[PDB]
Length: 529
Ligand code: HEM
Ligand SMILES: C[C@@H]1CO[C@@](Cn2cncn2)(c2ccc(Oc3ccc(Cl)cc3)cc2Cl)O1
Image (cartoon, rainbow, N blue to C red; front, side, top):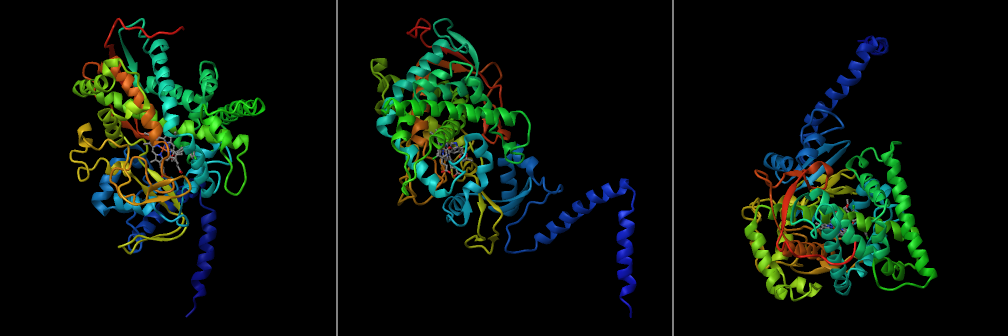
């Protein structure tokens, strides 16, 4: 009864392995891991403390291809197969999706020890924005940075911004080659060209100030284009490989951040610290509660983060608003009547107050954000094993949880006819969001305690957006002026493009063109150029 007989042949077997032709070693190095993860998945499927894991053929890659291309379709299939909790493998990671209001509650209100937003995002954002801020710092510092940024975003701030944002829109109509309203009465624009430029011009002028706005009329603008391109989903897998767009990214980050510090330091040494923009505001108020101040570099990187995050959400949203209204002249007609009423047929200048008396305009933003959430997925890295309540599931640490409020936005269950663009579903309900009950404060002010609203455009919980009022102000002024100046429609046989999900921001697949006409061909925008 000898067992060695075989253990010898284990050893012999290993030696015949090392000596196979390289033709076959490569083959074996491919077939053996392939077979291994198919065996592992069938085995994983028997654990009852695990959400179902979407089956996948290629290891490591996982379901990345279909997830990246059509994530909402991927969610609906996996939801029909396995229900509202499931996992799937994604470019090296396991994502545990939790669909629906309960998923919102499980992830957005997760405990600070269970999940980390900075662990999921810092690789994507820190090379773009800079160091020491946002996701390159502990959550407590985040909460106080949001407290600083919010302080420049007050109602009195927004009254200053409305005329500046409006001056910027008119100047863009006057001077941009896509309009030139003093020279042409009709034209064709790509909204994916016009809207990003309008967003940065209005955002720069109002948040950063006139100096920073002015710099975008020079070769400097290309640095924002550079810094923009470093903000790419393959920052999320290959974040610092030594290619050149990784360098123009880091150069633009250094160069842009340098410009803000120059202005900051020049204001402190001229004592020229007013209340004109977010730069004055962060200068006067950026000391943490433990007494540490933000450095001028940390302040500037927080500005890059503000402008950059606002840039992509806002520009995509005004692009969808225009594309949706391009086939709804009835809605343009209704929005134009409200403009005429609230503003005495133009004999009243637009103020932040009159903006709040325009519920149908605000309903259009509301509705566009329901059909086109700019972020289809939000993530956390799981730090501690989490038991999914009223199940037997344990999400072990090292997984990621993925919440997707914009998927629920498109469910007939929660929005009758969810795929119709209908601003009237928000009749007497035009608030950008509503704290439907009890509130909580995480460091940056009282926000809703529950995050179980099926309309959750701005998320909830500690990582909840603080830009919604700024975005409504900016989009509000922009669309008010658009509506009062132009009608617009599609070229023959064109309609609303489908969303290009691969940028992770749900942009219209460009080119997305509209044809605009002047409501008053003979009208002239003033000022010099
Ligand atoms: C249509 C406009 C916008 C939408 C739909 C939107 C959406 C969101 C969402 C869903 C989050 C939560 C992310 C998460 O929990 O994983 C968020 C966070 C945030 N957003 Fe917005 N956003 C918009 C505009 C803006 C603007 C214009 C700004 C700046 C002026 C801004 C600044 C922020 C900040 C600072 C956070 C904090 C993230 C954190 O605390 O980790 N957002 N936004
Ligand atoms: C992955 C993350 C989730 O949300 C965003 C996208 N976004 C959301 N609203 C606007 N942009 C995002 C959110 C905020 C942000 O910038 C700041 C600015 C100030 C503070 Cl105090 C904190 C952060 C940058 C991004 Cl890129 O990406």
